[PDB]
Image (cartoon, rainbow, N blue to C red; front, side, top):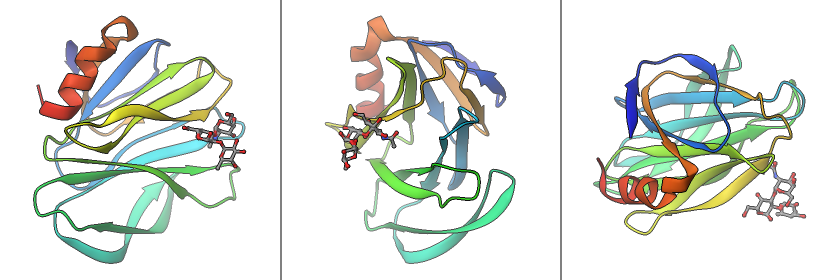
Length: 160
Ligand SMILES: CC(=O)N[C@H]1[C@@H](O[C@H]2[C@@H](O)[C@@H](CO)O[C@H](O)[C@@H]2O[C@@H]2O[C@@H](C)[C@@H](O)[C@@H](O)[C@@H]2O)O[C@H](CO)[C@H](O)[C@@H]1O
């Protein structure tokens, strides 16, 4: 567990989980290959009835629909658009009272933990084909090597 790192932008090295620790509901982080994937994760607090919320994604205000029917778990939602003028679309969610999410660049992909703790797992990915894909995090984060995926899984499901 290398960190915390302060919010920043980076060419996230391949084969590291970026375990992100946001402070509260809102945008958490964005990333892109600049070609055909612009992705973002947002965090929704417990007890949110279906609604639109405004996020600044790719520099622009976007109204996205969110909900969280848990009274204890936060919900991370992973949104992806495929072109600059496209639509950010929900692909995956992670429900967790421990407030942590993680993604990793590996195998020409970005892997992402999804499901509901305490058996969330790294079962979603998108294809990026760009090992220099850039990530900008508004939150503190940690780096965990892929060799220690089992530990990242432990932290996702139980906190630090
Ligand atoms: C958004 C993105 O980059 N998608 C890739 C991705 O899509 C896969 C992947 O998300 C896995 C994760 O478990 O789930 C599916 O296999 C998904 O496949 C895509 O979506 C489904 C609904 C089908 O329409 C399928 O034909 C489609 O490929 O990886 C694939 C390669 O496996 C592509 O690279 C997508 O663009």
